[PDB]
Image (cartoon, rainbow, N blue to C red; front, side):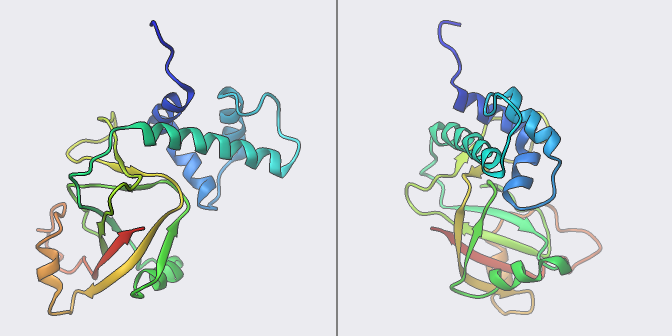
Length: 204
């Protein structure tokens, strides 16, 4: 073409199609194999040669993150949106500390990975988040994907922060009222009690 696609747009495109798993593993301090990572940093020109320090490899990962975020930020914003939604499983025993943070009003939860949400649907889970958006936030609607359909995806850059506004458990008199303002994936199964709580939070 007349123009070349920029490294940051190309990094987002790559991230969205293949890279997202690895990268988020690294960001979230979860296990991951350095071999596919280093290869990634190698083939995408963040390292010209195998790293010789811990700071050298982390420095390159950061550059890689910074390109994905710059390509994300350049997508058109959606100021018409006011809420996005996410379902998640806080009742897994290895997430008790995460659960503890999310269920305390006033607490701020920091997501180290890129945070994925939808403006159209929250898949039924033990917890649903209704995420209120401020003007000018960094979330952006992505293009159609090859691997799913049926809902939009709004992706946020790393280090997005969520303040807990309110916690409404399934036993609360407020539960159905809040639930009737959250679009869910189908909750018409034989198991009527999948959703344990709804949490309103705000992107800071």
